[PDB]
């Protein structure tokens, strides 16, 4: 889950 | 390559959307790019479901409102055999049960193409020849949050540690010289009210400012 | 009718453009209305050439950078059999020789419809049922040049002597009462840096403020  | 490009002016881009309080920018960046490629293929602009991606792509490595990546979304659309429309699978900005319906699919992809990392000219070529491109960037700054107009340039930006997915819909330049004051035309997913009607001009050919060319990709339709 | 309308959210409106130092607002207002009517007819939003209107519609009574009229622009399109895309016939903000080519045409019209003059309720009905509407206004005040946000109201505004063509893309109201603080949603052609990212809210139902409903029209496609 890196890009928010 | 053209001195400037703006796919919004050719019918490839849907109106600006809003992810609200959910970490789904990766899903809006992916639907943006697939909207453009589906338009290039069929001539029809159809808004695509970010919610379908948020609820259904955990197997591919996404985490819904807790984060994700555009390449994993395109991988999901390939493995799944389709993606539903925005209309039929509406956005609610919370993790919900996957309700993918094949009868409502309006898009497909066979995988995706990656732009060479860090290469702004490779990205320029992709934007000019393909259509809108999904990209990641460092948006972790109050200067971005309250951006209103002009070419955005942030000294504290990183080209390596990125935290937001957006869509490059074109590039351009200010003034009469096409070789200076260059910018990337970027569509955000914070609503039309944010920025410049939902868009931001990011400094172009200034050492990969904010990482725009670090992790760019587009779906193969 | 709806208490609010915003055609930008439905795919009818191209990005904000900039006429620069050429008195061609009439051509931007005309392409904006033709863009919305061609989108309604085909589902494809394609930017149209103001330069084609500036260089080619002198026979219809327009005067290029020296001014003109949206209705003469729609007459030129009907008489000429077509109008080129902005991509094929780029804007340079000066009067030049006509370069129209039918092969590059992406729009047509059979004439135009005039809204009842002076009737803001007639204009509200046309905006709600047709799409963006071409209108003329009194922009000859410094308060308009320096407008930034909020509902524009200029005490010295004329409803009869108009000097600028713009595009009404919707209407709405501020506050929680739909009859309170009403406004027209207007796209200008002075670039995204002017006003509210290129748009302005003009006071609505305040006696045809600034002449917004005096000379409104749209192309028939
Ligand atoms: Cl990615
Ligand atoms: Cl007119
Ligand atoms: N993000
Ligand atoms: N104008």
Image (cartoon, coloured by chain):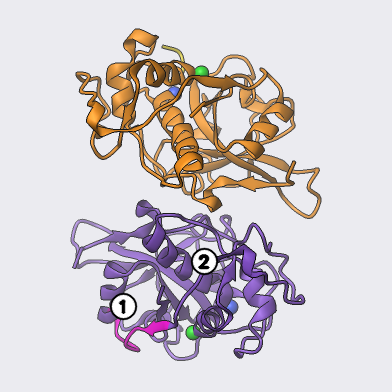
Chain colours: A yellow, B orange, C purple
What span is in magenta?
C112-120
Label 2 neighbourhood size at 10 Å, few (<14), some (14-19), many (20+)?
Answer: many
Q: Quadrant of residue C169?
A: bottom left
- Within the magenta stretch, is there residue C137? no
Q: In this image, B18 relative to B55: left or right?
A: right
The residue that appears at 45% across and 87% down in the rendered structure is C158
Q: In this image, C27 relative to C66: left or right?
A: left
Would residue B155 be seen by someone viewing this image from the given angle? yes
3D distance between C-alphas at marks 1 and 2: 18 Å
- Within the magenta stretch, is there residue C113? yes
Which residue was labeled with disc 1?
Answer: C123
Mark 2 secondary-structure assignment: loop
Q: In this image, C151 relative to C88: left or right?
A: left
Which residue was labeled with disc 2?
Answer: C188
Judging depth in this view, the residue of B169 and B176 nearest the camera is: B169
Q: Quadrant of residue B216?
A: top right
């Amino acid at each position: 889950k890196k890009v928010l | 390559l053209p001195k400037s490009v703006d796919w919004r002016k050719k019918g490839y881009v849907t109106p600006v959307k809003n992810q609200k309080q959910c970490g789904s920018a990766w899903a809006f960046s992916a639907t943006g790019a697939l909207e453009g490629q589906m338009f290039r293929k069929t001539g029809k602009l159809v808004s695509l479901s970010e919610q379908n991606l948020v609820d259904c792509s955990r197997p591919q490595g996404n985490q819904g409102c807790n984060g994700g990546f555009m390449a994993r979304a395109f991988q999901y659309v390939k493995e799944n055999g389709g993606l539903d429309s925005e209309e039929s699978y509406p956005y609610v900005a919370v993790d919900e049960i996957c309700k993918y319906r094949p009868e409502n699919s309006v898009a497909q992809d066979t995988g995706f193409t990656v732009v060479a990392p860090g290469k702004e000219k490779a990205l320029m070529k992709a934007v000019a020849t393909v259509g809108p491109i999904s990209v990641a960037m460092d948006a972790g700054h109050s200067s971005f949050q309250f951006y209103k107009s002009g070419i955005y340039f942030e000294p504290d930006c990183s080209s390596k540690n990125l935290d937001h997915g957006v869509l490059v819909v074109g590039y351009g330049f200010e003034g009469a010289n096409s070789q200076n004051s260059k910018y990337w035309l970027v569509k955000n997913s914070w609503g039309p009210e944010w920025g410049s009607n939902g868009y931001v001009k990011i400094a172009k050919d200034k050492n990969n400012h904010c990482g725009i060319a670090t992790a760019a990709s587009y779906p193969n339709v």
